[PDB]
Amino acid sequence: HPLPDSVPESEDLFAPPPRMQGKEGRPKPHIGPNYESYVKEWAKTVGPNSDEWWAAKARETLDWYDDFKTVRAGGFEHGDVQWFPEGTLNAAYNCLDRHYYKNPKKTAIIYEADEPSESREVSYEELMQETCRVANVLKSYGVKKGDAVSIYLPMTWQAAAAFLACARIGAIHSAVFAGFSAESLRDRVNDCECKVLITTDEGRRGGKTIATKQIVDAALQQCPLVENVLVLRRTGNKVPMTEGRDKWWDEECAKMPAYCPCERMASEDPLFILYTSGKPKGVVHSTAGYLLGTALTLKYVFDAHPDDRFACMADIGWITGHSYIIYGPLANGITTAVFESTPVYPTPSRYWDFVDKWKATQLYTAPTAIRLLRRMGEDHVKNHDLSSLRVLGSVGEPINPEAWHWYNDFAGKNQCAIVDTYWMTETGSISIAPLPGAISTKPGSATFPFFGMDVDIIDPQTGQVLEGNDVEGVLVARRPWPSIARTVYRDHKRYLETYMKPYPGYFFFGDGAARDYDGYMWIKGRVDDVINVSGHRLSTAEVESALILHKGVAETAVVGCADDLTGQAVYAFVTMKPEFDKEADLSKELAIQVRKVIGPFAAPKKIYLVSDLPKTRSGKIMRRVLRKIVAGEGDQLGDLSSIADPQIVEEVKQKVT
Amino acid sequence: EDLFAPPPRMQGKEGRPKPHIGPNYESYVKEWAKTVGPNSDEWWAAKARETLDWYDDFKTVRAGGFEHGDVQWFPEGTLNAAYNCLDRHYYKNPKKTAIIYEADEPSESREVSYEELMQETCRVANVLKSYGVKKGDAVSIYLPMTWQAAAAFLACARIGAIHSAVFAGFSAESLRDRVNDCECKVLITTDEGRRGGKTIATKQIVDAALQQCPLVENVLVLRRTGNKVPMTEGRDKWWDEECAKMPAYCPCERMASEDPLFILYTSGKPKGVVHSTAGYLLGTALTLKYVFDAHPDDRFACMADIGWITGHSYIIYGPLANGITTAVFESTPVYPTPSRYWDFVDKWKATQLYTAPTAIRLLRRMGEDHVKNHDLSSLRVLGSVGEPINPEAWHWYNDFAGKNQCAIVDTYWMTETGSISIAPLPGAISTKPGSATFPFFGMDVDIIDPQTGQVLEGNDVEGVLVARRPWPSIARTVYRDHKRYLETYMKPYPGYFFFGDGAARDYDGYMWIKGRVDDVINVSGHRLSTAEVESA
Amino acid sequence: KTEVAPGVHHVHPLPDSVPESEDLFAPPPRMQGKEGRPKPHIGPNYESYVKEWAKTVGPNSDEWWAAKARETLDWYDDFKTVRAGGFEHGDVQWFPEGTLNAAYNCLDRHYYKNPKKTAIIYEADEPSESREVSYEELMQETCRVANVLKSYGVKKGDAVSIYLPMTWQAAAAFLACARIGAIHSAVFAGFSAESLRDRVNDCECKVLITTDEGRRGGKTIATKQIVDAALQQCPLVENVLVLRRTGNKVPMTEGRDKWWDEECAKMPAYCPCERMASEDPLFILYTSGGKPKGVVHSTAGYLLGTALTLKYVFDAHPDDRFACMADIGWITGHSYIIYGPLANGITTAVFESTPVYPTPSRYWDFVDKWKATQLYTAPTAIRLLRRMGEDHVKNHDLSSLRVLGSVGEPINPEAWHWYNDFAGKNQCAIVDTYWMTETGSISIAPLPGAISTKPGSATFPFFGMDVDIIDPQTGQVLEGNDVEGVLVARRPWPSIARTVYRDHKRYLETYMKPYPGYFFFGDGAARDYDGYMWIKGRVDDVINVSGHRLSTAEVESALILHKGVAETAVVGCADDLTGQAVYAFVTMKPEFEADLSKELAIQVRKVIGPFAAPKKIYLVSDLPKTRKIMRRVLRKIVAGEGDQPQIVEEVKQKVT
Ligand SMILES: [Cl-]
């Protein structure tokens, strides 16, 4: 395989902390205690004899109405991926019934309402009962196995009941993020051809009202196939209701029994459609492979144990909510959080009040949330307990070291593992991530592939695989995995052309990646944490702090590069405040400012004054881009479609060259 | 003080089959104790797997409860009621009589084999599939007491359709109301009925009702009499001509245990009692076997109507599930004369008889010359269903129909319990005239003071009858009105099932059913007696 | 009398042994496991056949059939009961509690074992366009079409009409219906617009699968043009899926008509299988011809019958390459191109050309190119090639062949010996097969490794078939050898047709009522002194009316449809204008002239054609009979030879 045999120790690696060593009374990790223990198990899941491992894990992890015989078949070329094809199962049975039969009063969902005082625990019994009522309502509307049902719901716990009610009867749910405009909701409702929509009267988030039902009425004026709308009374405030079409959730459910049989679904029966954010692409996922993928990743990537309380702060309208709020945790039979507020409502301490109130054991959030909390100050977090946490997760954009260390220092008090996850709607479940009890982390690196994932780097100019470490190119996967998306709804040609045609024989993620000298994977390039100039270890944060002391400086970002004289050299990008008016003199003046603070050896090799730093629409400084420009790769920077002002990159290249 | 011990015909003597449970109260209590309490899953799991044939085995025995009405039994299992009432007995002995069809005119009677019943059932099922009937669709049935009514019931069950039987004596308005409630698109009925020498204009009433039932698209009409009736082109087709085009076999739909089997509306806003498949079928099969001590060659005669729950459970589902012979009696107790019941018993050698106290009192007041000179020795067990039988009728039943040689079985149950809830097991329990005696397997009943809400422990107590735990054949909801289901049976005495009937235990623990409970309004957490307010 | 088990015996009308002689052709070395060829499944003599066959009928046959069902097919749910029902009411059941899928057994399970193995040898009309279609490719195309059909709302139990020529996608269309539980109804792609309309309307399908054009023998078949003509009288059809076989310009109706490749390109290349009960209908196949009879076949029993016959009658082995040169529009293509061979997981041929295009060497070029191991064709093809000369075959290799099959009609000695001498070079077994659409699979045939053959004899019944001969005048079975009568079967067999679609009464009256207790094949048969079975051919008189060959029986069939007619008899006679003219003699029932004659003629024109309308229709008291219509007499009376039992005198009076 392209993976290392061992990873030598260094000061750039953060080894699993004691809470991930089975110390201090915490559970012993599922995989541990070192890199070798990861690669030993991973090797069983790919290559020649991997069928045996997947067959056993499939039968151990999920309950089946009918056993499977074949483990896998098909491939990328024609998009006929199959996993466990002869088997039958039901996603609601595996996420609800089987746990309800074992421990009905166990909490399935921690519902943290927008207002803290309205939060409560929802048991597996209560969740199963509401799921069965809604399922029965859908059947009364004529919903059949294979019918699409659109869901336009905010982050209330009943959204899980809506998802699983569709899965329970074999319907295909299509969740629409509850912040979407009427046009985006319309486009998704029409493409899936649903006749039924499940929505709410209003949403509540950050103390503000979301006029879901008003937006629905506007969209449905251009959705002629929709005949039934089920409306949850989230707020009870007055909203328009169309006679016949619109019915109240509580009034319909009260008419129905609180149990409903499960439809026996084929492994490859479609479980849901999820349209990409933005003609949108309906990503289609099967039942068995997707369910197994989410169950195994949650268990192993977050080291989940039977009594854990998992807090994913995402939205069910996106794939992260599908896989790591609803399906992954409930399949494992643990407690999962549905978080309805924002990270700063009522104050920026909300996340941490939440963790300490429920004693959450894992937290899964996005760098954009961490960036918001970083701006609000340390006082909102530093005096909390938070010791119930063992694993801190990050998902979304590539995370920069400064945010990583803030997350590590304050959310984890340096006692949690940071699992940086890479995946896509189309992968179904986490694709590259450290196993927190085995893998030593680097700030900004996803590390090593998950079970079933055999990834490699391809030179896009030649199409050939790059062998060895310290290589960089585009990321591809060599073989199908259980939770891979199976098609694009009614547009299979687009599925093949987008993912399978660019590099025949491979799955094309669409992202650039680098594999560093130790074999660690870096999505969209390597980012610098600490740079070693002439034997001095200097953190980008240390240098940037010295630069900002100059009152004229607004923002700064420093990156490193190999240097024939000092080993590695520091390159600093600096933007001045509007209240400032020679360029060379300022650069010399800034270097002295660094020398006075840190030392005569810490002066950056180059200081570039630029109008603005390159950022994405989320505000993330693109330090990886800057690193490549310094390395001379300004003509190999990638699509760069995420940037806010794409001219800034061109300005940076001119200054550097 | 009367106490009648199991008589010789129920002691394994005179070549009669030995009773399944016997010989005394201790033999009943020994088995019953296995069916209630915290360790009863073993017994029920075993009885479910031995009594019924399953396509898919179950894992969970029971779950859910009264509070929210999420009662589950054998949830992961699949089965088919038509397979268990027809196919499996056809495969064993196709020529065995499934139905003794006693027509309104005695000379038009005949035996209907399992083979004939299965083939007609299959033909009808194929017709329903050609009409577009799918698993889960409701089908209304408006049929009189001819043997094809069973084929109609079991045709719906065979394909997973939900049949809704409407008593063939109902008015157009009552039939209209029940057809529209279930929203069925297909109706099965007859051109005419015949009962007591008089013609029942079923099709004329149907045409009146369907002018106000816009959802009905297909009507299947049996030629019971062949007399001229109005037929609507397209909508109405003849049963025999439709079945003549269809094959004589039809595959069975694999049904989940909790899939609805049928809706039965209350006698009368009609209330649709819904029963699922496995639990109901198991309950009717076990009660018939044990309450009536039914053995493979027995000939069971329930003199009820398939339009009521008694006919659902103890003409069709219970007896046919056991593979024995069941009776479809199309006449009255006194046509052509008041000897009709007793002519029937001797002509077919009925082994058990299940009738209503009203018919017994009727025949008692017609004189004993109509019964006293019959044979009737084929009988072993005489059952009574309905209001509790008054002692005077009990003794007439015992003296003349049984000749003091049969066990008398008074039964207590309701449409909502699915199967017999309290009754003496004929080979074990010494009976008291007018007493239901002791609860059936899976039934754990108690008496509560209607005011305090508390259990009256001990004996010589009287109050409201309640059940502590769900049983397999309990009704699962009221069709599209689950809130009425909870409010009627589950909210009056939280934690229990409220039968709605008064009851008393005597010094020996025998139960005595004491008529309907004085309606008690619950005014914002206060239970009020309508009788006390009237007093004030 | 053969022992089936220790102490158990079966009493059958078949011999116990067949003595050797020089008129019998014993299995040749290629069928003796010599020269590296596979050892036969049943062998080496008659005794080995009767020993196994006796287990499949008679006392303990349930055990044998249960094991073969579980060995031959993959089941989602096992069965409990082996067989039930019977002829009287048409409630035949086999393996009723079991569930399976025909597409899973013909595709998925073989694709999972060896995806690159060739499923179909597609011999295109033009040789240069022939190629091998793997199980992978076939499964992918089957799943795409299945997904397309589901998008049209096709559900389990819905009929789907198929009007496809002999391109390999025809198998994908068949199996796509089987995969989702739909009932396919294949219509021979040579049928007229009227014949297609009648079958599309009777099965009430809402979906039709066809092609833009067909290609056969260098000629184009305007399938889509014929479809457009037929669908103007097919109101239930809403979706037509059109395969681009040629890509040349054809009409397309917006909305109704969609291209196969464009629809399939939108769909995934995998599709789950519907779990089907053994007795769920698999397909409708309409008999060739007034009112067509839709023969319905179930799933499990039919599939097992085709699987076992293909394996044992042709001694197929895992890597064999089976070449059935029939058409998928007929039962022989259903059973021995698609279902039988693919169920066995072997390679099967889809032959799109004729036996003489581009030359009469096509069959033999085919065998030598693909190394075909068995060949299955019709006596009309063998006779045709025989007339084209020996040079086209005598210098080919053909040594890959082991078994040569014949189906369709009695094979005559000249054809049998030509087939044996040149196609087989006297080194193949000749298997002469008898069966019908209604039997599902071969009913009487020699097992090639056990039975010594006689040219023209089907020989002995297949597994599960217990057949006998009945005197049609008495209804009683004829005991012993050297007997002649009508062929009947004594008990149901797994692949027997279960009904006639929406006409079960016609099913019972046609097959189960004529000889109660038996299945009536409708064919004459004889058992010779050695016990070998010989099937009698059908009789057909053909007259030449205005250059068209017209059968007398067809006209009689059209005339008798009028329920007032009791009997009818049509004869031909010289006519100065049409060459020969049609003269119909008609007798009416007691439950009944100018208008009747005109009405009967119109009915004949509608069914057969305006050229078949009788020139004269004679209403007579009774047709002249002996014991058998005297058609010779009627011809002479019409021709004016009345100068060469009283009804005959009236007939002459009526005619003149
Ligand atoms: Cl395995």
Image: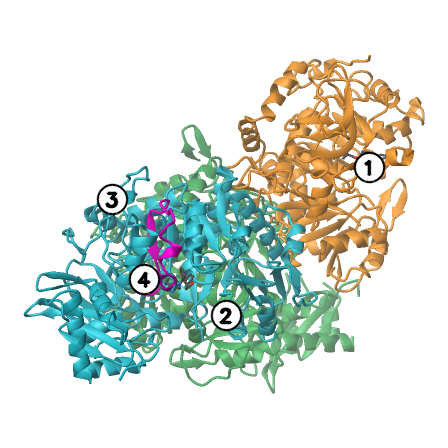
Chain colours: A cyan, B orange, C green
| Amino acid at circle 4 | Gly
- As displayed, is residue C194 above or below residue B379? below
Question: Same chain for marks 3 and 1?
Answer: no
Q: How far apart are the alpha carbons under marks 3 and 1?
A: 68 Å
Mark 3–mark 4 distance (CA, rounded to whole Å): 32 Å
**Distance between the alpha carbons at the discs numbered 4 and 1:** 69 Å
Would you say residue C475 sits in the magenta stretch? no
Which tag, 4 or 2, sits closer to the chain's start?
Answer: 4
Q: Which residue is mark 4?
A: A75
Which of the chains bears the disc numbered 4? A
Q: Position of residue C287 (x, y in %)?
A: 55, 64
What stretch of residues is rendered in magenta? Answer: A374-399
Looking at the picture, which amino acid does disc 1 mark?
Answer: Asp
Q: Residue at (73%, 30%) from the top-left corner?
A: B453
Which residue is labeled 2 in the image?
Answer: A180
Report the Cα–Cα distance between label 2 and label 3. Answer: 42 Å
Front position in the image: C159 or C220: C159
* Residue at image location 63% in from the left, 81% down from the top: C610
Q: Is residue A398 magenta?
A: yes
